[PDB]
Length: 425
Image (tube, rainbow, N blue to C red):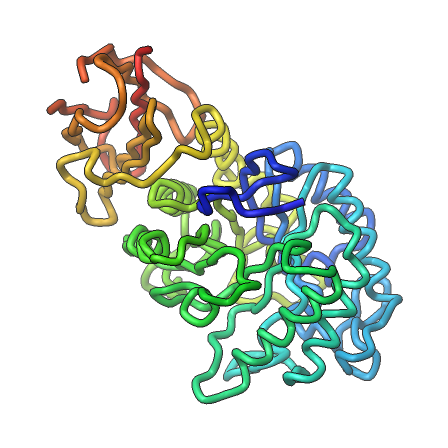
């Protein structure tokens, strides 16, 4: 179903351009019964999402705390012997998401089942032997599903001088064996924050189909450099932010001094990642991924129970980013910072520009004015517009000869605007 584009910068769904729009639902299989999961999936489909990242061996004591129907995932906590009773619910949620046109970003396991670290519950069960057997059992079970994109890892940097990299590579094999070829599965890796993303360990790996980042969860960080670093690699492979700052998440993991994120944050992450080269974007909400509920232990102070948190504003605004990207020639899009004079503004007021051949999007993060170099896209005249990332509306500026300074309608904190340039022909 899912392949890399011919230009090796985007993903396809049955040959056609596929826009990755993700919601982060780590504990979906772990904490949502059949009625809950139908409720969550039907709503997210209405909001124009396409990817749902979820974890089979969840983070919240995923092995020893059973799913809503009382079943644990691994018989004797042994990865070589998964519990078919638990994965019957995994089958249900995968098939339900397919009914809503939703692709599951499937994480075979959270990282704490390999490396607990100081905060993980674990217990650690994976080695280089059972990871492959585990990966094969999953790949053989779902080799005929058409709405699965595989996601190894889970918030754990491979420990130096360890078997961690080997374990993930062994799990990638067996997955590839289970489905029957590198072509029969799309696979990436979810990392902890770093400067190279998952590509730090797996970029040259034949099974590694596209790089993924965890940019965040801070404010004013130059996330465009992280995307650019993977885009400018001589080995061309697509790139995406698999975990930006979450809505209703403590800023920089420091709520005491810095409080809680806002919708402006999730929009800045979404547009800066996309305009720097990302083929899509995964949205996340602190309340959603952990499925915040009064009857289950939470972490890191979520504020909205998950049914309400689905209606948060940042969740509702990602469809505007989807609408914007799909309006113009998809495969021709490229990051081009030479499109403006102020190509290296600070993150808080970043001017980030993307373009194809007959169009150009330029994101002004704090609504500051920018001057655009006009020798860059085709045409002798160019249409100009403003696109409101909060509501998705568009307003006309003028038609300009193809060097020119533009001013967003408003400027200041929360006044992010994107300029739409179009070949008049």
